[PDB]
Amino acid sequence: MASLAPGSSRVELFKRKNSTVPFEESNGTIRERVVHSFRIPTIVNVDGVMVAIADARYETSFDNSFIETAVKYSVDDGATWNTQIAIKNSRASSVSRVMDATVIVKGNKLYILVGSFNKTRNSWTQHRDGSDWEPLLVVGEVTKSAANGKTTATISWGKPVSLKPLFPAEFDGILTKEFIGGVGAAIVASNGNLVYPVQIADMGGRVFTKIMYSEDDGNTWKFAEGRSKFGCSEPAVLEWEGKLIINNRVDGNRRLVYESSDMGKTWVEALGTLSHVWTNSPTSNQQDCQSSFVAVTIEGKRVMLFTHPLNLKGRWMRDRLHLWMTDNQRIFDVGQISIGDENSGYSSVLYKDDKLYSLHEINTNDVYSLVFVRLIGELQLMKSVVRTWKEEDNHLASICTPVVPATPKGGCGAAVPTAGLVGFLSHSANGSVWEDVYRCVDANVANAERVPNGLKFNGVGGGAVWPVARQGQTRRYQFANYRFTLVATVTIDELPKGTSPLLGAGLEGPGDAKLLGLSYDKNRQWRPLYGAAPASPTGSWELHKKYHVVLTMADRQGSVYVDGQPLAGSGNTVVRGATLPDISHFYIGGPRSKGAPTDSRVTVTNVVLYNRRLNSSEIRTLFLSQDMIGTD
Ligand SMILES: *[C@]1(C(=O)O)O[C@@H]([C@H](O)[C@H](O)CO)[C@H](NC(C)=O)[C@@H](O)[C@H]1F
Image (cartoon, rainbow, N blue to C red):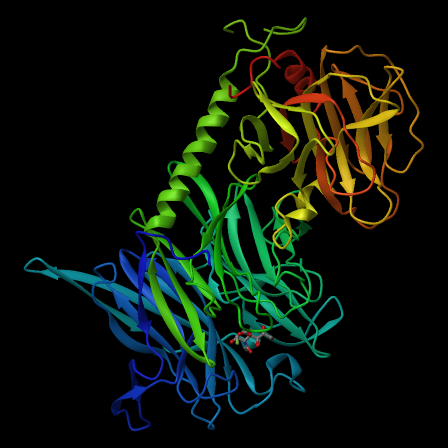
């Protein structure tokens, strides 16, 4: 189906039952040994040298088997590679193993944290105690040099050091058992700290994540105070605008994402941005998978990249590996980078010298290879999208809005708000799709006719659905359940028989409940909808006149503004309970595929969506600049 893009290609770099590694016998003799499966990929850039790290599972692909950490490195961007076994296992039994490498690059050093086991045949979280385990830190040093035009490099690996003595016996009364790195690429924070996200198993077997960091290049390590809820594993971390963003694997439920502004001391779920957006399968009740999560700069803009399989086949098949790019506001699906319906798995992404690559698993009959992918077609699309984002943000921020009684300048009022601006439906549209100017989430349309910057509705179900929970598996507007601002310019074209819908956020579930919204009636009054509260008519409007509508929701309170002023009933609680609402979609006009044959004769233009509640000054600015923001 969707797949590795034209222009892109790949090679089977770590070839199952084919590629050999320099296995070192007890006597020190080296033997090129065949490897059943290569798993747990990570590819990073160390001073210009590509370094690929992986589990070499010599005899079988099972987790509790004979495994050592293999490395392939290249000084020519993948033209050629050298192979080493960077970390040996204990050689204690037929199942001794060092596994699940988590890597940090600082300068010309590579810090690799692995889980080392001697003889257990069951899963690490299920062990009776931590006795078969050791968390091992290994430092590698990359040295390159050129003699007569040819550049080559070597990598020396230090002796492993166990961090077991630094592991607290308890965290808040929680008795600890074992811990392993989050798997994949970790980071050096802006303050120089080595930051490893770790997964901790407690005695009873619960798992949760934490930040383990070093302020002195690995001489000492500290476990920060904060942690994820239980149930989180294989965390990936990146630094964004002064905060650590921790993206967790969650078997059997949606992926939790946290932010910490204080080196992991305090964690706050990112309910307004990325938490619960991604998941393990269409139904979310399947085994989840490791994901890479890296911050990069493309076309002058800082963005985050995230990889994860759709896993339509379920369990560990992990078919359809996708790559997403986000600037913490918009979330773009770059596409599927694996091929057809092949099984993929754990993955890594790297942006080096303006070229994008991936190292990821492919699985056939549970025999694993690692492919090295040149994401050429994908980078081209990413750059195009980032240019769209920059261009539209700059354009909007450059509009000279009208001065207000307390302004100061090129004689312009406040800038049109662009911070937290997530989607925008304006001019571009056809008969079936109203395009998101930011190219992420389009709205579906019915019985509509184009007008400058929007659509005029006429017909049963005429209107548009901007999907929220209806996006399905990946819920990019999941933030709306926590807070949002929806804006639009509207005209009522023909009087309704009784009451008819105009704009709002619908809720999943029976009946036809709304979280917040606005309708209009035959008496030419507005009918704001505040959660489940009885709607009472208020105010006055006239046919054919343009009105500005703003819906705000934050802290469970909802307000509805018409022409910059709140309608009666605004400002009260719209969601009772502690459980987050579950918005199905935002409706524009009166869309529907069933139930009452709604036919709202209205025209709507310039629909803007923010992931926060706009303040009074921003609402006034939008009200005053309605004629200036359209893409027409
Ligand atoms: C991944 C995998 O699902 O494919 O699973 C890890 C854990 O088994 C899983 O998170 C449950 O605890 C394996 N790691 C270990 C140490 O078991 C990974 O190696 C990988 F197998």
